[PDB]
Amino acid sequence: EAIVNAQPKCNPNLHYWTTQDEGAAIGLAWIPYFGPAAEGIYIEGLMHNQDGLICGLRQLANETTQALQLFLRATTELRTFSILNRKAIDFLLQRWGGTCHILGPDCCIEPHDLTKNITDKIDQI
Amino acid sequence: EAIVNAQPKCNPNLHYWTTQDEGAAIGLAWIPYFGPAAEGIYIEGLMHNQDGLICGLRQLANETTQALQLFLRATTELRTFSILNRKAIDFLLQRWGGTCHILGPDCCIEPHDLTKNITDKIDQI
Amino acid sequence: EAIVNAQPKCNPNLHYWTTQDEGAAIGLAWIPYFGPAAEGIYIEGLMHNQDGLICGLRQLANETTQALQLFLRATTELRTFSILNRKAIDFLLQRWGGTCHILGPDCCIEPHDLTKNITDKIDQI
Ligand SMILES: *[C@@H]1O[C@H](CO)[C@@H](O[C@@H]2O[C@H](CO)[C@@H](O[C@@H]3O[C@H](CO[C@H]4O[C@H](CO)[C@@H](O)[C@H](O[C@H]5O[C@H](CO)[C@@H](O)[C@H](O)[C@@H]5O)[C@@H]4O)[C@@H](O)[C@H](O[C@H]4O[C@H](CO)[C@@H](O)[C@H](O)[C@@H]4O)[C@@H]3O)[C@H](O)[C@H]2NC(C)=O)[C@H](O)[C@H]1NC(C)=O
Ligand SMILES: *[C@@H]1O[C@H](CO)[C@@H](O[C@@H]2O[C@H](CO)[C@@H](O[C@@H]3O[C@H](CO[C@H]4O[C@H](CO)[C@@H](O)[C@H](O[C@H]5O[C@H](CO)[C@@H](O)[C@H](O)[C@@H]5O)[C@@H]4O)[C@@H](O)[C@H](O[C@H]4O[C@H](CO)[C@@H](O)[C@H](O)[C@@H]4O)[C@@H]3O)[C@H](O)[C@H]2NC(C)=O)[C@H](O)[C@H]1NC(C)=O
Ligand SMILES: *[C@@H]1O[C@H](CO)[C@@H](O[C@@H]2O[C@H](CO)[C@@H](O[C@@H]3O[C@H](CO[C@H]4O[C@H](CO)[C@@H](O)[C@H](O[C@H]5O[C@H](CO)[C@@H](O)[C@H](O)[C@@H]5O)[C@@H]4O)[C@@H](O)[C@H](O[C@H]4O[C@H](CO)[C@@H](O)[C@H](O)[C@@H]4O)[C@@H]3O)[C@H](O)[C@H]2NC(C)=O)[C@H](O)[C@H]1NC(C)=O
């Protein structure tokens, strides 16, 4: 399903902040006693609207809210951290949750090299 | 392992309540400020004892308690939400955690279409 | 990457304590009301330095600390329980996250039995 930014305006540049699970710690800065405070753990980046991604991302986050709010209403967890790991499991289940019938449309097995390697095995005669 | 209901009685109908992660929100009812209270998020259903499922389910929940209690004794989490996602990971690991030897009993790959498609490739001569 | 114990000393024996998710409960000891207190849920074992595992394990835990501390700095969870389940998902994603090209180095499918079973199918003539 396509994404159409229907917002009054779009800031086409995303000046973002985030963290990294393993920065390049210099010396003892990785030790919590010596490391940065809560305010100094962030990295920054700047992404422009190539492929209309930024304006599409703003619209996607807007459209996601209804389903996300309905999900949070139905969970008893106070803080939800598992949405992404859940997507990864459903990703694997939708491809490998059942028997993989080679050449079927829902089986992500490419047997081309196997077939030729077996095909050219008869090329002795 | 089969399930034998050994309870003094069995209520053969399951009038159940649950939630749905995405109901058919009408208008602004998905917005938490406008939506239902904690008491009005539930849906209901009624399931009868077809295939003896309800009486078997009551016995299964009874038999599950020992293993479930022993699991909860050994975990340090105050609230456990991960039992089902854990089953899904172990489900995938038991089938795809190692090399899939085609035609072996523990490899869920059906190569039938591949074999015939290669077999009838020799039917030119 | 190899592990070289660079510690001042190594205790080459690991007298360890842990729990088991399902011990052999005798009678009603699995019932929390009747079972052991928090102090009596532990089992013990003793492992010696076969294959240099114990001294290697002490060095590994030492070397793990920097990456583990940097990970904990970047997470907003107060208590992290998901590192191992995360490794299991990444384990499956690195092998089955994309199309499995048979005979490729990143596809863990062994088609040997399939090939011979197809090869000796031509042995009628
Ligand atoms: C995702 O993105 C969409 C689109 O941007 C967001 O939609 C907005 O939804 C809210 C409802 O939650 C709307 O609020 C209502 O606004 C009306 C009128 O607002 C007027 O002023 C706006 C500010 O300038 C303007 O943008 C509006 O323009 C459009 O819409 C009108 C139709 O109303 C249309 O004729 C125009 O041509 C524009 O297309 C509009 O001029 C206001 O009257 C509402 O108030 C009543 O209802 C609420 C209950 O919802 C009640 O509390 C009030 O007391 C009052 O009774 C209400 O405030 C908002 O206007 C929408 N914005 C747009 C641009 O459509 C959506 O919210 C985003 N989702 C998330 C999760 O962020
Ligand atoms: C899963 O399902 C099973 C089966 O329904 C549940 O098993 C029950 O286990 C508990 C133990 O935790 C039992 O409690 C004990 O009951 C005895 C005697 O109970 C009598 O009265 C019952 C109520 O009517 C009746 O059902 C019983 O009937 C059967 O059993 C007797 C053998 O005792 C047999 O002869 C009959 O023919 C029936 O087959 C029985 O008539 C009671 O004396 C016990 O008390 C002592 O011990 C406890 C410690 O456990 C102590 O605290 C007391 O002070 C006292 O010293 C105890 O109360 C219960 O009887 C079992 N029910 C059945 C039907 O077998 C099991 O609990 C379920 N699991 C979960 C997690 O829910
Ligand atoms: C993983 O394993 C490694 C190796 O065991 C651990 O490394 C240790 O790192 C800490 C830093 O966090 C070091 O602390 C510093 O120690 C110096 C000097 O210590 C002296 O005394 C030690 C105790 O007997 C001895 O082991 C040391 O020996 C070696 O190192 C010297 C070089 O210094 C070398 O010449 C020798 O031949 C040995 O190889 C040494 O004799 C001390 O001066 C430091 O103090 C200053 O700096 C700190 C800031 O870090 C500051 O707070 C102080 O006030 C002071 O200004 C500091 O205490 C420790 O010595 C290292 N140990 C070894 C054996 O190398 C590492 O910690 C482990 N990781 C985890 C997570 O556990």
Image (tube, coloured by chain):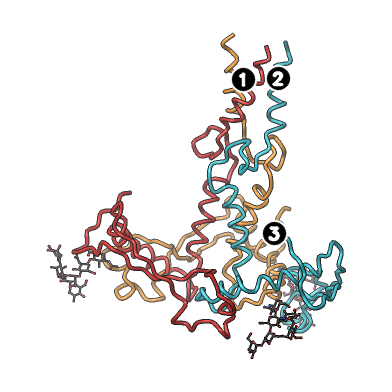
Chain colours: A orange, B cyan, C red
Return the chain for callout 2.
B
Residue drawn at point x = 86 percent, y = 67 percent: B49
List x then y, in percent, for residue B30: 75, 74
Same chain under badges 1 and 3? The reply is: no
Same chain under badges 2 and 1? The reply is: no
- Distance Cα–Cα, label 2 vs label 3: 45 Å
Neighbor class of circle 3 (other Cα within 10 Å; few <14, some 14-19, many 20+) is few
Q: Which amino acid type is marked by label 2?
A: Lys
Say the numbered circle drawn on residue A119.
1
Task: Provide the residue designation for mark 3.
Answer: B1
List x then y, in percent, for residue A21: 43, 63
Neighbor class of circle 1 (other Cα within 10 Å; few <14, some 14-19, many 20+) is some
- Distance Cα–Cα, label 2 vs label 1: 9 Å
Depth check: give the residue in front, B122 or A48: B122
Secondary structure under badge 1?
helix
Q: Which amino acid type is marked by label 1?
A: Thr
Mark 2 and mark 3 lie on one chain; the one further toward the N terminus is 3
Q: Quadrant of ligand 1?
A: bottom right
List x then y, in percent, for residue A17: 48, 66
Residue drawn at point x = 31 percent, y = 76 percent: A33
Say the numbered circle drawn on residue B121.
2
Secondary structure under badge 2?
helix
- Distance Cα–Cα, label 1 vs label 3: 46 Å
Residue A114 sits in which quadrant?
top right
Contact, mark 2 vs mark 1 (Cβ under 8 Å): yes
As drawn, is B65 to the left or to the right of A40? right
In the displayed structure, would residue C5 be above or below residue C75? above
Secondary structure under badge 3?
loop
In the displayed structure, would residue B78 be above or below residue B124? below
